[PDB]
Length: 572
Ligand SMILES: CCCCCCCCCCCC(=O)OP(=O)(O)OC[C@H]1O[C@@H](n2cnc3c(N)ncnc32)[C@H](O)[C@@H]1O
Image (cartoon, rainbow, N blue to C red; front, side):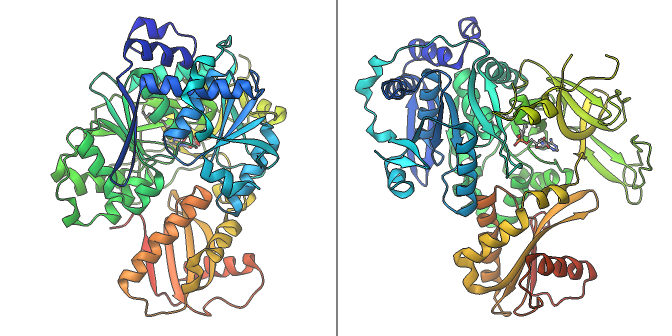
């Protein structure tokens, strides 16, 4: 980031070490649970990392070995992650395998990455193991690690191109893809983030984002640690239970940067009653980033109208685009500036070119700019491999020192994504994303592959239905079905449930809708957009999820079936 001595460091390990010498008592990370606060300084973070690394070394872990990190959000996850890096080990973070699908995912990650050790908290060695082992991997409770081991740490010779950690992406549920992020990849992107976000020493980051997804890890934890900036955090569970707490904490801690995928702004609008806004002051919040999924004008306008009386300014909104394969940040605008939009015509014909329309012409729709290329971005036709003109839709191809090394132990998939070559032309990351450049700003339009097809091959509908049927929620329900609907230019994950009691009162309905949203988010890392409640026995008898699902999809579309209530995330 800023000071030259830090720019010169060759890994995040040395950045943390040096910060701990220059400013041992500077607050780094704060984690919040309810009204409880725990903070660690740079001196502490460095000492914990050394202690953990010395333990890994004492237990036979070698540079390049993978160490699985099984943690809920919190300071222990962050200590363990740095501790892995200090040992030259490849960190492999995973969500605690609390339910069936999360456990299946963990097993597939273990099989792929073949870690030598797993770290987790003492409580979890009891919950997830029978020398304790988790899925045959020797396990170690982080609490067993004492600070008197710190001085035993032996520095390794970390090279730029060495892999620092694996970040597993969503999708590919059947063969999870572990993106190999090198030490050089990581520092390159951290610098791009610090710079592009105009961070400085007033900056304070707040995050509730999953630390097991790139944005919440690389953006909201590793960047602040790298840049000497406070990270103030809570768990996604805390956010979903009480989204107001996000805005309360931003208020209390005068956070300047905080953000999320687009849905979370709608979730705030939907969940926070006018009277509960009393006490907010969001004037400090100058960069409200919006990335990881399609960015919606309507969402941001709703949020702006809902919070403007409490100091929130629409200019704070900062659309951005990226993916794990490029470490994180690929495009973004200028902080404090108004993001741009374009209005496309209903009819886009077949030329792959963008067809524009007057600012509210019939059937027109708006796309939000994801900002300027920060990594090099080319729009390339995915079939012919010929570059697209501006205002012509093609695949988003990326190149820079932030582009990752491949997928762990998946050589064919790695060639499929990281070896893009332009017809008659460098090597590019092929994102699978479609979009276009207009006046040097990137407009993301969709995915090459049909999202309904993707949901299907990942077994999302069947697995979401399983979750509902196996949660305590099933006690007030009959049968259920989950599916994705494409509905003018957007995709909406839709859940339909029979309810035993068709007179379910408005409060119970609201609670039920929220419980459903939380369940799917936790079990599947997906966001439900629409929930429909219908009477018992309203779905025909069948032993087939597919038949049941097709019936619900078809009769939602008909507008025939009896409906008890509907919930729409993005509607007021
Ligand atoms: C200090 C904070 C700085 C944080 C800077 C954060 C910058 C945003 C980086 C998000 C990292 C990413 O989401 O990871 P992942 O690999 O799981 O999935 C990536 C996929 O998601 C999609 N997608 C992300 N953006 C999108 C956008 N704008 N429009 C539409 N589709 C977007 C794409 O399809 C993409 O391929």
